[PDB]
Length: 423
Ligand SMILES: Cc1cc2nc3c(=O)[nH]c(=O)nc-3n(C[C@H](O)[C@H](O)[C@H](O)COP(=O)(O)OP(=O)(O)OC[C@H]3O[C@@H](n4cnc5c(N)ncnc54)[C@H](O)[C@@H]3O)c2cc1C
Ligand SMILES: CC\C=C/C=C/C=C/CCCCCCCCCC(=O)O
Image 1 (cartoon, rainbow, N blue to C red):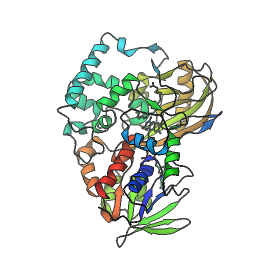
Image 2: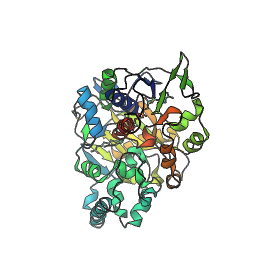
Image 3: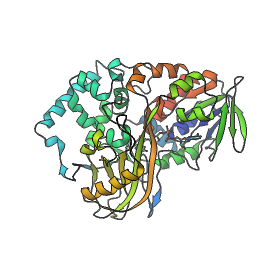
């Protein structure tokens, strides 16, 4: 437990940091400060304007099991009121097909899925807990495909891959199953499969903008932190405009990047240096032959097709001159990084192939996405080490790396961090 008059400095005004403020405030910790580097809040929930409506450069959707996000909507008064999500499936040559009608693959998938469901509910009980401080089963530390191979459920990858690889989280040849299954737990997977998906008319960013406004201390923006030191039981935060002292540090920003403006200790340097991330690239496009529906391309989710468009988003049904966003990955451990130029050429070429040629790209973003560690690093005890450092020199660790790269997970983690260490 931590004293209620502690001065608590929260770095980052994305969901993770905003929720930290919310839940600290609600537990009676009123002397918090959220420091944001940019001029805006919401982080990767980023919904800019175009032609009188908001489009999504980052996060788009949620599922009914997003309980922490419902608590936030309860507080802001926002509602799930966005346009309905609908999808078709394309081959890499633009051909529309329906995977579940595949007479060989169809049955293999449903048998694997059913078998996995049973395994998850028994053998792997506890897998779905938020965070990684409850040590998961050792099998879950293997790359997702190996985890499946071991259990004779390879064909379950067909259902899990679409809202995972296409959604920027990487490839099953290497991403530890622990991550896959805390995000796509059986319930969430079934919700997605069923199309039971939340969206917001004013963008996922809106509820975070409004959360910020409801906070007793809305974020301080445009804060360029040049150095943080932690001597004598205090946190000294140096910025370009001021430097100040706190009692507690909550990190919701990238931890490898933290090493560069901090008095990082040996463990912090050793362990945070192992963090790897996804280079997930979005392009906001105007197109001819406006799609009628969103399109996924399982062929382009293969590592051999890295940099190609894996999915694209049909948001506003009624205006053929509104924004269609495309999604691609620029990195894989077995491959050298694809350049943004070569990938932007693939956006144009792929969309042309799909029959929805691009007339214009008006915004582009490669995001710092899904920070995580390797299976080898997971197995070697990365989370036991880092969770065991919680509170060392009044510093706490949070955000995506500590849970999973989605807004419900990071908010959930921020909620429990207060329960775990402060209350
Ligand atoms: C294209 C895309 C689609 C996505 N789709 C979904 C989806 O459908 N559903 C879902 O749940 N999630 C989705 N996500 C993931 C989700 O947006 C993120 O997991 C979530 O925003 C993570 O929040 P965070 O606070 O942990 O980190 P971030 O959102 O990355 O925010 C971190 C904040 O800290 C700030 N910061 C960074 N460095 C510093 C510094 N040194 N000093 C001060 N501040 C700093 C940043 O500017 C930012 O405001 C998507 C993301 C992208 C990019
Ligand atoms: C519950 C969702 C959790 C995390 C999502 C993370 C990332 C999503 C990234 C890009 C999503 C691409 C949008 C494609 C439109 C989907 C419409 C549909 O599938 O029916």
